[PDB]
Amino acid sequence: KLQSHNFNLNYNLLDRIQTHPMLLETKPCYLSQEESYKIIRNHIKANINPKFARITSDYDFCLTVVKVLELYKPHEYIVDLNAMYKRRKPKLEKRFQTKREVEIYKVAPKAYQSYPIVEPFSGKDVEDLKSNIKKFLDDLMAKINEPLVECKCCKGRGVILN
Amino acid sequence: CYLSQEESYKIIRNHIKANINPKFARITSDYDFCLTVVKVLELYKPHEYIVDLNAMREVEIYKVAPKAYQSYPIVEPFSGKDVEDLKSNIKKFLDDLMAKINEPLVECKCCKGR
Amino acid sequence: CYLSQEESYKIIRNHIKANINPKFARITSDYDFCLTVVKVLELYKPHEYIVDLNAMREVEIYKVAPKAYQSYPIVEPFSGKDVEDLKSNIKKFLDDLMAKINEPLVECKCCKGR
Amino acid sequence: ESQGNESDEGILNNIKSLTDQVNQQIGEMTIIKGFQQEITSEYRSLKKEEVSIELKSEMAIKGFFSDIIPYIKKDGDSNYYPGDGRRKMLSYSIYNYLAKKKYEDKIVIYLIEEPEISLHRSMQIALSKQLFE
């Protein structure tokens, strides 16, 4: 059946000596750090529903996807365009917003700002590693594709399945 | 004997800080020029965050300022006929106000907090 | 099995803010890098400033910080052999810590709190 | 030079916490986070260096002492102003204030050259009283 894997993988330095290279695939393995982040970033770009969630910052060093939820009543509030400066007189302006965006998932291949570092993918077998990647990949996608309407009974607060 | 604007704001701030129910509400901004109270939209109080680790919309009630500052509401200077009229008026104002702050949150039905 | 240095600080802050009793103790510095809760060296709780208008040394208890910051005592990472053992340890430390902070003030005896 | 008591020390530490929170809050803005994230990518594309670019207020980094300045505040007015003649007059009171309590260990000689330049004649008489009376 062979490895049949496009992505490269690594093994423990100590346990390689006693084994054979052809027998390395069945032994426990872990994926690379940047490789793990690259896999997650590439799948997210291809799989997220644009309506349900929006990806704000995708970079080689950071990744942020936020959840877009629509408030049934169009939210209206007042903003100040002079709020960045204290001395001059305030000037008010009306703004209507309908899609309130909340941060859901964010990750980085390495320590950058406050982003959480992605953990490397690990598996006892190359196919076991693939299943672990697939299961976690589907879990993340499922969190992204959660439906989004706000409660009429529960004004404000959060979301209800739809 | 009408209380002025500044010390009227002082007693509300001191009373709010003194008797508040942190399980039900919290103070975000506590400044001599502005005061903000928000509602804790979160569950029962004892050790909720301590159990979810094992498994591994903001709202405001009262805003007040002694003087015009940003968009904060202006505090009203307490007025009354005499000293005991102030004491009665101030007392009832604080309780009805602060009952609103410490009022237990609405379960809100269909969203059940989500 | 031990919790992270920052995570250890995070839970104490969130839970201290939860059950804090404004009658006995007050939270002064509440920042992502430091935390300082002091006692209320003051008399009975309800309606003192009100009777004041009718008439007409601060002590810190807990100081913690996730990282070395100013002179704040450093936080300790919750370490447990078993995760449930850690959960029992984290709870016991918190009640011991927070029963201390809610302990009613001493009567002050000789100087009568003056 | 002035003595610092414990209460002032507590206020000094409290201010440092406030300025730190200001810098932390700046980094929490979306437009600030958006710019510094992409400008980091632009820099990384320029040169493969492992750095990050952050926007912080200069005062919050150096400390409140770095940019503290006197403000001539007219009584009954809440506005703070950086007039011009009052600046010249107040600049002399700083010299007056320092003269009293700055150099107690040396002989201080003042070389005042043409003080009347761009000075109102009423202020010239005021300076005359300071020099001789």
Image (tube, coloured by chain):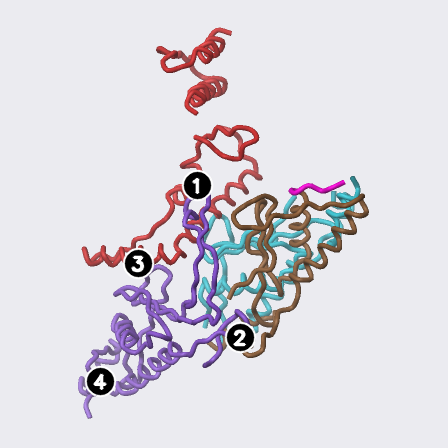
Chain colours: A purple, B brown, C cyan, D red
Q: CA distance from mark 4 to mark 1?
A: 70 Å
Secondary structure at numbered mark 3: helix
Q: Please indicate whether residue A116 sits to the left or right of residue A152 in the image.
A: left
Question: Quarter holding the C terminus of chain A?
Answer: bottom left
Residue C14: % across, % down: 54, 63
Image coordinates of residue C9 in percent, x first then y, are 50, 61
Left or right of residue D52: residue C19: right
What kind of residue is marked 2?
Lys
Of labels 4 and 2, earlier in sequence is 4
Q: Which residue position holds label 4?
A: A24
User: Residue, x 66% and y 50% (percent of image)?
Assistant: B14
- In reply to whether residue B2 is colored magenta, the answer given is yes
Q: Which mark is residue D37?
A: 3
Amino acid at circle 3:
Gln
In the drawing, does residue D110 fall left or right of residue B11? Answer: left
Q: Mark 4 falls on what kind of element?
A: loop
The residue lying toward the viewer, choosing from B30 and A3, is: B30
Q: CA distance from mark 1 to mark 2?
A: 41 Å
Q: Which residues are magenta?
A: B1-6
The relative height of residue C109 versus residue A13 in the rendered view (above or below) is: above
